[PDB]
Image: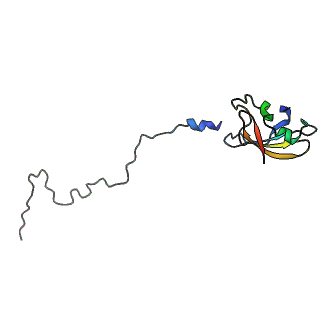
């Protein structure tokens, strides 16, 4: 009988897909980086 | 005076989600009755296994090609419980 369609099952996949997006940190190391800084402002002296 | 030997299936499909088409005799070689007699209320009751609960081969909306001893016409099943009633088509 076609009533079998009422007891149909569905399959759910456990592997999720994250939308196409950038993972960031593309410019890491591209500029002069100072790690472990402290304070609200960091000053870089410059000479002419 | 319904005779099971004179009823036959027309529609070949086994899909029970749609209607079926039947053909019934009634000419001199069949049950030998008029179309009006065959189309009377409860005539096809003997075809159902249990007409009180509407259990049987006939379903609502089926098309029966009735072939009486005088004329012939298309008929459509309207109800199957508590009687099998048909209307012209």
- Tell which of A47 and B58 is nearer to you: B58
On the rendered structure, is B31 left or right of B18?
A: right
- Tell which of B62 and A36 is nearer to you: B62
On the rendered structure, is A3 left or right of B57?
A: left
Residue B84, horizontal then vertical, whole percent: 75, 36
Which quadrant of the structure image shows residue B55?
A: top right
Residue B73, horizontal then vertical, whole percent: 84, 47
- Counting labels gives 0
Residue B37, horizontal then vertical, whole percent: 85, 38
> Which residue corresponds to the image point at 77% horizontal and 44% vertical from the top-left?
B87
Residue B62, horizontal then vertical, whole percent: 74, 42
What is the residue that sits farthest to the right in this orientation?
B28
> Which residue corresponds to the image point at 79% horizontal and 37% vertical from the top-left?
B41
In the rendered image, which quarter contains the N terminus of chain B? Answer: top right
What is the residue that sits farthest to the bottom in this orientation?
A48
> Which residue corresponds to the image point at 89% horizontal and 35% vertical from the top-left?
B31
B28, above or below B73, in the image: above
- Colour treatment of the image: rainbow
A43, above or below B5, in the image: below
Which quadrant of the structure image shows residue B32?
A: top right
- Tell which of A16 and A4 is nearer to you: A4
> Which residue corresponds to the image point at 40% horizontal and 47% vertical from the top-left?
A17
- Tell which of A35 and B4 is nearer to you: B4
On the rendered structure, is B26 left or right of B62?
A: right
């Amino acid at each position: 009988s076609l009533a079998l369609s009422q007891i149909e099952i569905q399959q759910f996949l456990s592997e999720a897909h994250a939308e196409f997006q950038s993972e960031g940190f593309l410019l890491q190391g591209a500029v002069r980086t100072k790690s472990g800084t402290k304070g609200s402002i960091v000053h870089f002296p410059v000479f002419g | 005076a319904f005779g099971i030997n004179y009823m036959g299936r027309v529609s070949t499909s086994a899909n029970n989600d749609t209607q079926k088409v039947w053909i019934y005799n009634g000419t001199a070689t069949g049950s030998n009755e008029t179309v009006a007699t065959i189309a009377a209320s409860g005539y096809f009751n003997a075809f159902m296994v249990n007409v009180a609960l509407g259990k049987g081969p006939l379903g609502v909306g089926d098309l029966i090609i009735i072939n009486g001893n005088d004329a012939s016409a298309f008929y459509t099943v309207q109800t199957i419980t508590p009687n099998v009633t048909v209307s012209v088509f």
